[PDB]
Length: 301
Length: 318
Ligand SMILES: Nc1ncnc2c1ncn2[C@@H]1O[C@H](COP(=O)(O)O)[C@@H](O)[C@H]1O
Ligand SMILES: Nc1ncnc2c1ncn2[C@@H]1O[C@H](COP(=O)(O)O)[C@@H](O)[C@H]1O
Ligand SMILES: Nc1ncnc2c1ncn2[C@@H]1O[C@H](COP(=O)(O)O)[C@@H](O)[C@H]1O
Ligand SMILES: Nc1ncnc2c1ncn2[C@@H]1O[C@H](COP(=O)(O)O)[C@@H](O)[C@H]1O
Image (cartoon, rainbow over all chains, first blue to last red; front, side, top):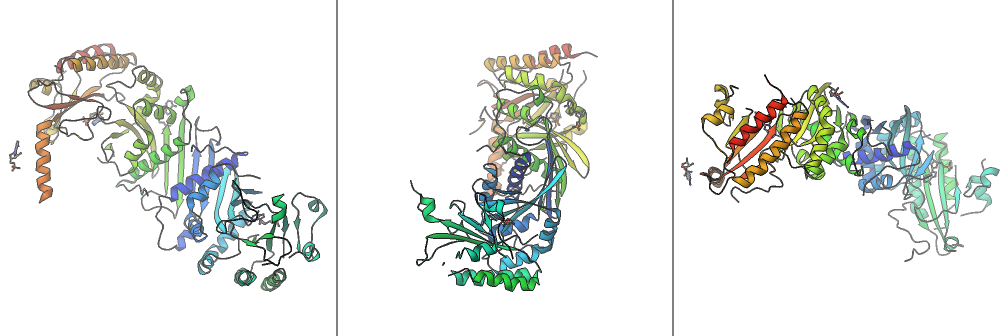
């Protein structure tokens, strides 16, 4: 129960130290009756300078900045994520291999750019109000936190989302969906990221579609009102039988944790679990929406 | 469980914030087999800028420095203080009293000190530690628990935290400060409810502390080690702080206190009230005393001061 912050790179240690520090600080901050406009222009900044102290895993000097901590904490709640669990997932052991997941595979940690953080600030109020209005049920990425790490004078920005894939069920094939297809090198990768054409070709498909579609619609409409585009539908495929070849039954999962998961219908060829959510809304659009919205509807049932 | 760090002076809020913050970080830092020489030049430093966030009680901007945290954690241990207890006394509720504070539960004293004071702590720290080791924590000396530097509105403030020389429960009805010439309470001092009396008062009122022979010896043996140690460090002009608790007077005071509301006695855990001594079963009055050396930090010398200081107290007791 002693949290060393041991990690491969020091920046990951700082991240671990950071999430720990801020989540603890928040536990002393009252949950407010509503977010306020300043909450969206707020930050926490902490600077550490430790001389001859506690430098076994942490750098002696580093900065850690959390953007809009009241907003992201509310988002956490609206996504049904407990702060202490969020903290544990980041903090209990180093994140694993810019794109990481927490060791328990529940949360993804993505390095991003100055402008991305700008774009997020740009959409945050609306994104929030929408998560409110849609009562949390949505295929959009779920933003759990956003941070700036300063290590060795270098700034690094990170965004934490909920993993689209199960944290336990092994994924057997990945499709990026918006003309485009998979490259040789990639087609020669342990887990290849296929694209639209490799899908219609593979005749790949089997369900929920009614509620997935009415959900996905509202989303893309939202992304249009924000004049965003060029984003994909990440689709995951877990082949139950394959995985099979004191128990953890095949195709078994906690829908409250693997939030994007749907089991295959009865009349489905091979028993599968699907993972689907919208990814990368951060960086004709009004048409991208209607186009995207239908290319997807043709991959269900 | 929510701690708001509510306190009159933002400085106090920050003190609470800092003791809290540092104690938790220490909890994630393994306990070493021994202290290393660097631990005595070590420090932590944290600077906070909280923009439009979390400002009910804390300033948006402040700095907290803890000197030699490894050494002070270990000192706490040697003194039988648990870090959670310590943390809780500082943070559960604001310190009471700026220059001279007690934690809300009266376990710990927090005093503002000068930069010189802080420098003198470093000078003497390696030796003071060693001494605390070889006397097993058994000492009339001030028991140092933490040293800190707070920055609020660009203004730096140094603080040293000690264990209270007095009981955290038992009332003091009379205190003294003793050195060993021409010392006594001013006419202004006496005007206070709890006047701080001095050497010629203690003598001119013919006071004696009746602790009995077994205690008197155990006490003078401590004093002897402590004051010599203080000699070798060339340290001078420290006082013996003397508090007196009148058991019967207190029991009546308690009674009166309940009667107001409506409309054991002389007992102390020697592991908490560490300087306290029961009066001999043959004293004229039922009393508890508290005696400790105070002001180690800041015409003869140290060797003489130790000898003199020593022989005075020796007489104070029976
Ligand atoms: N395992 C994952 N869980 C959640 N999101 C992911 C995952 N892998 C990739 N993404 C998102 O998908 C985008 C990249 O997908 P791709 O480059 O098509 O593999 C990035 O914005 C990621 O945030
Ligand atoms: N490691 C140290 N050793 C000796 N003196 C120190 C040390 N650190 C600080 N001091 C003294 O403490 C006072 C205030 O220190 P600070 O404000 O931390 O720089 C100054 O008189 C310093 O010289
Ligand atoms: N209860 C106490 N515990 C520890 N030190 C004290 C206590 N009361 C006073 N002092 C210190 O003893 C010296 C004389 O304090 P005073 O009672 O104001 O004369 C000063 O160094 C005070 O900071
Ligand atoms: N048992 C007692 N011992 C000593 N003084 C008392 C006692 N009871 C009352 N007194 C004092 O007599 C006065 C009247 O007390 P009270 O009975 O509370 O009005 C007060 O000064 C009390 O302090």
